[PDB]
Amino acid sequence: GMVAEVQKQAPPFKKTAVVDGIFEEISLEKYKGKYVVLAFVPLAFSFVSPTEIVAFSDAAKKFEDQGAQVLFASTDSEYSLLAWTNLPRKDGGLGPVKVPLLADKNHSLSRDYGVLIEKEGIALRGLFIIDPKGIIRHITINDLSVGRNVNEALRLVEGFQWTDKNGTVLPCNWTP
Amino acid sequence: YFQGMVAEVQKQAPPFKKTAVVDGIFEEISLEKYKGKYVVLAFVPLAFSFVSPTEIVAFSDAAKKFEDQGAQVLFASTDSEYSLLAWTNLPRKDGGLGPVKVPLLADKNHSLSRDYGVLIEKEGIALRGLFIIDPKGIIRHITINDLSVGRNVNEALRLVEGFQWTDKNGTVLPCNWTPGAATIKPDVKDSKEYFKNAN
Amino acid sequence: YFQGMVAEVQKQAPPFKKTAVVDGIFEEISLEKYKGKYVVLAFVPLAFSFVSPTEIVAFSDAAKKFEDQGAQVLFASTDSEYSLLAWTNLPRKDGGLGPVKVPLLADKNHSLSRDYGVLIEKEGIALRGLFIIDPKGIIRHITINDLSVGRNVNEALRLVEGFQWTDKNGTV
Amino acid sequence: YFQGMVAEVQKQAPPFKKTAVVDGIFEEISLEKYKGKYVVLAFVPLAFSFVSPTEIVAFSDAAKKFEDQGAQVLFASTDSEYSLLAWTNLPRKDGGLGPVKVPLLADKNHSLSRDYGVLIEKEGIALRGLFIIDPKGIIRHITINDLSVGRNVNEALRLVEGFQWTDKNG
Amino acid sequence: YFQGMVAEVQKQAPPFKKTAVVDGIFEEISLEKYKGKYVVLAFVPLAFSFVSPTEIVAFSDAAKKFEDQGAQVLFASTDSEYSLLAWTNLPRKDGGLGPVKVPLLADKNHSLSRDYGVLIEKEGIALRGLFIIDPKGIIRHITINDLSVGRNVNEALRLVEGFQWTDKNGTVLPCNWTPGAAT
Amino acid sequence: YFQGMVAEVQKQAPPFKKTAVVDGIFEEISLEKYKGKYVVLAFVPLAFSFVSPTEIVAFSDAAKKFEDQGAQVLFASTDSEYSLLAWTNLPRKDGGLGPVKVPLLADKNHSLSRDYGVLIEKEGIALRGLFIIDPKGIIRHITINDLSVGRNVNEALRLVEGFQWTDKNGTVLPCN
Amino acid sequence: YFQGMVAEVQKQAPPFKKTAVVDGIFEEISLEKYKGKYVVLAFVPLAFSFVSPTEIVAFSDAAKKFEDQGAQVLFASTDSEYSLLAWTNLPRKDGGLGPVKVPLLADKNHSLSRDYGVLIEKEGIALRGLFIIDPKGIIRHITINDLSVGRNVNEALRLVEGFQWTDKNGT
Amino acid sequence: YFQGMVAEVQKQAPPFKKTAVVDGIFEEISLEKYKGKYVVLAFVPLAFSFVSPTEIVAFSDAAKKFEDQGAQVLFASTDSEYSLLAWTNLPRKDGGLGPVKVPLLADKNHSLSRDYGVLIEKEGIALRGLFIIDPKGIIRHITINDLSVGRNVNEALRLVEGFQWTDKNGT
Amino acid sequence: YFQGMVAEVQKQAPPFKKTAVVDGIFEEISLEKYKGKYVVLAFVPLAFSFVSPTEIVAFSDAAKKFEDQGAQVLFASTDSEYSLLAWTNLPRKDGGLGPVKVPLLADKNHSLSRDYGVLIEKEGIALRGLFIIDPKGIIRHITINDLSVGRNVNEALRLVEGFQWTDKNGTVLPCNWTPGAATIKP
Amino acid sequence: YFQGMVAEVQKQAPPFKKTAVVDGIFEEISLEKYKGKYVVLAFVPLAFSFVSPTEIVAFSDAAKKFEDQGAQVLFASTDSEYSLLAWTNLPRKDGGLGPVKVPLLADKNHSLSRDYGVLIEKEGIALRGLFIIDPKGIIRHITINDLSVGRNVNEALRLVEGFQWTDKNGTV
């Protein structure tokens, strides 16, 4: 019974995903050695979620510079997620994108990470930062009406990279 | 809320009543006391230790900015009220924190930390957890950091003002929203205006 | 009906109240809404999938025949209302579904699919199940197809037409 | 399959071994005896009743058409093999079934009906269930009718052909 | 008696209510219908079986003797009422039962055979049990026969007349008395 | 047969080993002692009381007829072997059953009555049960009478003879 | 007393109601019938046995001495009332018991022997137990012998006179 | 015998190993020590109390007779071995017990009295029970008196002699 | 106190009612008899042994000092009232206890030792536990020694004086107050 | 000892391994470390509490006397090692504990206070318990005082000598 918690090992997974208009299986294991930023969104074709995906996608290189893979996830199917990329951003779609979109249709991923609203069948806006050994170092969970902050995710990755490399709490006046 | 339950977003916050340090004397503080205001509840692991001084100082400095958004900030740890008092009293040279403008709650029996799901049982201390609780007692946001990196007081403010907004206006806030930025009406037709002006 | 029960022929159909796409808007649809009418409840596995659309159009094209027989057709899948809505806005030629004349019920929390015993738990999707519910809420018929093969709209009509003749005449 | 389980699309059909009536004499029929073939298993509620004969006759008459699809039709009911035999020896004019081309299986202890989820427990009879089983023993389709309306033989043919086609191709 | 109980001598007979074939039509027969009377419930072999209904016609031929002693004979099997009906409509010369003068109860859900402890669960048929139930619903005699051998109708009458004699008078009956007395 | 099991038609009869009165002395009788023969086991409720003498005498007087059919008759009650011995030894003028030609088994501990389903728990006596067990130990027939009406020795005879015919024993006869 | 309890000293005696042979007839006997008297309840294993007869006889003979102590003697076995009567109808010289002045209780359903803790389950017979029950229903003494050795009338009298006395005088 | 079992006639006696007073000295006494002999195990409720010393002295005085019959007498109470010792060191005129020739066993943790079914739970003392145990360890007799009436040393002698005889001769 | 609860500091003391030797006579002693007073309850293992007698005499010799502090000493063991009486009737020169000025409670059914957590189950004797119980029934102090070392009568007097001072002079500072509050420095 | 077990006289003492403040630095202290020696484990007042600190100081001043008797004194509280450290660094002239000559163990996870029976669950603090443990690890003495009154260092010494003596000889 997987329950995502900070300081403990992330629940593993293997999910079908949309990777450049194509289906691919993605595991967490695939990315051992890198940091992973796993972000959940509620609903394909909804309102805040497309803006979040678009924002992290555009900063993909920044994450890649900090040695981190961004992954998104929802309880929608890989076909809905694929149609979602084929829909232009001006129409509340994603346009093509540079981060995988994992399909959690049997809800095991959201449940394992503790973000499933069981009455609705959707995830909350949960974000998890997972380190190269698979340990969860940070959790953010937002109620549905308020989007997350890309920079905050970047700050944290860089900060945990730093305290990992050096073996110390951050300097008194550290910034990214 | 029901006994045995851990803090969760969209659910009622675990109630509490704790002895706290408030301007150099002790005062009992309850969540109930603030029903009607937003509450920001932040945990720290240990008095007289590493990252927590900067965090507490940052949030205490911003206390006026939180009140201007109708929010009360509260800090908690598994230390006793006597240690927390000492922490605020002692000169800097004796590793003192200085007086702070927020209450410091003593969770020495560990019930608050356990109820909010931030206790490291084996260690007897809380992770760097932060909770935003709305005026009805519902948890709108959860942050939990491992111990080595601190939190960002500006993000906490952003988020408070964010839930105040969606509460007052019933719009919804895009990614990276700041106060005044475009918001979305959560209706399939009305939302299109936003997606056009944004692209 | 009792909670925890799965749909069975001769028993009260599991009640439900679901959000649905009706003519490009959202409407709440319960089973109870249709006491006194036959209901034909059809499940499909996946929006933006392949066999599901051709079936939904068969039945949509046939809505008037059912309406004549005093019957309401309903489709459901485990997709959200937003995905189902987008499906219908995508034209039939572009790989979409196009608009249709039968409600599309969103079973995102899986309760409907589970109550009717058509959920594939590991997949998050419903088999191709079809249920005929009579005016008193009793299930009179059950079809479940594996995923590769679509159903037959003339069978649905045949079966509705039949159960009405037998209800009305006392014979078989 | 695990005993205690009920028939379900995408899963292994429950196995069975039953005395049946074939062309006027008794014979044990099992599901195993038909691996490699599609199997159309259809239940009827009662021998010497009124809707079931017409159904059986329609499927009997179509017997060759199923054989041409790699398919074996079986009927079963909770009647004894002795009632089922007497049922076929009573000519149709006389209200009987007459002879037919399909085995009639006798589920007198009820295990088959219960395993396939068609038993009406308080009545001791089966509903009008029909199951399509592929050569590998997986149920590809389930039809269950209430008692007053019969099934469609052409639809069962249509389905078998359909699952064969997608089995081999896409 | 209690639910799930089985039939036992000195105890209350499990109640029942079953569709039956009577004079070529369907009728509902309960034990309650015969309060005040002795009831002889016999379980009989599968309809149309290769065994023979000579036992059934014996009790049928005897029905009025039981009647005259204030008893009702009932038969039961696990066949449907439709099968039993067809059985009676099939003349004996042709391999059937022909008409009979006692109710043929259809225990197609097997509850009767189970409650009376004669059900062979794996075959779905009943053994040839016979039960004598008095006017208060108490079982006074049980016979259970293997499927091969028959029961003796006159011996069942003897037993009825005996329990009647000993009920009415409070005596006991070691004496073996000729049955079939005219009344 | 398994332990805790009650006597049932078509199943193995419950084994037993009981002390019996046979021609004025004691003997151990087990069912096992009569494999190959039919066995007719009959219970009575009480030594020194009313209908059981007539039954025991009827059956005793017929013992040779039963032997002629390949069967052994046994009677049982919950009386001790001492009460039964005394019952056979007593002078009629006083109530003596007298000597009899069938064993009287002592079920003082009630295990026989219980295994065969005929014990009246509250009374500590057996109903008038009769069992016919075939040479293979299979029960073929059960009669149980309430206490006020006697059994028919001729019917037990008829029945044994009937089972000897179903057994055929090298003879093929018509359905009659 | 609670149901399923076994006879125990200082505790209330399990109640009973049993058919018995009294002076050649059948009479229901309960313990209640002697509330106010001491009761000496003795079990024997078997009618038409060998040790038990002589025990009952010694106790029937001395039944005078007992009633002079406000005490009722009662015997019991798992035999039926018909066996017990037959046994008493059969004279001693002929290997029986002969008539006796103390009731003989029939515990054919075994509940009495089981309740008083003397039933040999595998045998369906009672050990040679003897229980002294005071006027309030309290067991004040228990003897249980194995089958091969009998009891002693005088020891039962000694115990009755004794509890009589200490009850009267608290010493 | 199985753990949790209580002493019952025809069954194996619960075993024990207990500190005892044996002629002013402390000695461990087990039942196994007496395999081959009869054991008469007698319980008394309370050192420095009343009925018990006369009983113990009667049995100690008969020490001889019992050994003639090949039997060992043991007494036992829930008192400690220090109270028991002091009991025998207190002379009898001075309300003590004086010296005695039977072991005095100390059941201060109560397990012996519990196992032989004589412990009065609420009081922490044993009833006046006596057990005759044969050379094979089987209990052949049980006596239990309420506290106010004592036991008869002759009856125990009789019973031992009785079971000796039937062991060797049948009948 | 709930039933089956064991004695703990700050919690209600397990109640009891026991037969006791008081001045060569039997008397029923309950805790209730002494509400309003401190109670010092001390356990000893065994009548007619070596260490226990000198503990009892020490406390007996000081019973007036205890009375002056408003306290009652009670002693207890798993011996019976008859053994205990005999113990006191046996002079010390002869290896007994002598008469004493404190009750000796007979805990023969072991309920007292079990409830106060000092019973050695396998041995049927109490450890050397001492408990101080205040006038409202709250256990304020527990001491348990192994059998080989006796206790200190003056330490019990000390503790009672200490609890009676706390009871009359409450707390160190007023409610919520701190030494630093209401003061100004540079 | 078995896990879950509370400290009892005559039984093996619950083992422990705890971070401790010793001469102003952190060190792991375990019971196992003082096998051979007697151990006097005393639970103390919360760091920075308003109570007289003289109890702690008496035992620290007596440390050498305990060492002279083959005994090691330990203190424990539910405070963290950082609070304990700030407390010993704060001189008494400023209201602290000042440096002490015995280990201060931090039981911030409460296992020690719980294993030893002194934890007040509802308050997260230990009562003033004192345990004397012999070189085989057996608990020989227990004292538990309500929070308002102190322990007597002399009594602790007496008891240690008493047990040293009765172990070396046999008598009281």
Image: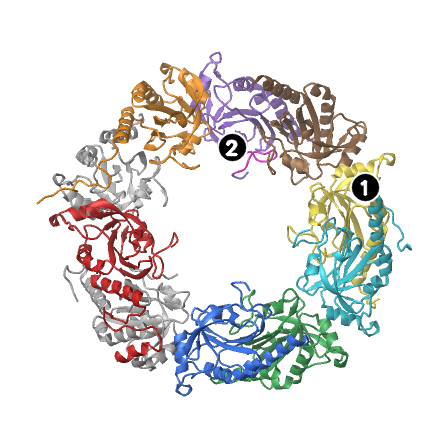
Chain colours: B red, C blue, D green, E cyan, F yellow, G brown, H purple, I orange
Question: Range of the magenta residues?
Answer: H4-16
Mark 2, Cα crowd under 10 Å, few <14 / some 14-19 / many 20+, is some
| Whether label 1 touches label 2, CB < 8 Å | no
In front of the other: F29 or D76: D76
State the residue lying farthest toward the right.
E182
Question: Where, quadrant-wise, is the N terminus of chain H in this rendering?
Answer: top right
Picture coordinates of residue B100, whole percent (x, y): 18, 52
Q: Is mark 2 on a helix, strand or loop?
A: helix
Picture coordinates of residue H134, whole percent (x, y): 59, 30
Q: Is mark 1 on a helix, strand or loop?
A: loop
Task: Give amino acid for label 2.
Answer: Arg
Tell whether H121 sits left or right of B106. Answer: right
Q: Main secondary structure of the magenta part?
A: loop
Q: Identify the mark at residue F23; answer none if there is no mark.
A: 1
Pointers 1 and 2 within a single chain: no
Please say whether residue H31 is visible from this viewpoint. no
Q: Identify the mark at residue H114; answer none if there is no mark.
A: 2
User: Which chain is indicated by disc 2?
Assistant: H
Q: Mark 1, mark 2: which one is toward the viewer?
A: 2
Q: In which quarter of the image is residue E80?
A: bottom right
Mark 1, Cα crowd under 10 Å, few <14 / some 14-19 / many 20+, is some
Q: Quadrant of residue I166?
A: top left
Q: Identify the mark at residue C79; answer none if there is no mark.
A: none
User: Which chain is indicated by disc 1?
Assistant: F
Please say whether residue B145 is visible from this viewpoint. yes
When the figure is inspected, residue F8 is found, relative to residue F26, above or below; the finding is below
- The structure residue drawn at horizontal position 53% and vertical position 83%, both measured from the top left corner, is C64
Picture coordinates of residue D163, whole percent (x, y): 52, 82
Task: Give amino acid for label 1.
Answer: Asp
State the residue lying farthest toward the front.
B168
In front of the other: D138 or I101: I101
Q: Does the magenta stretch include residue H8?
A: yes
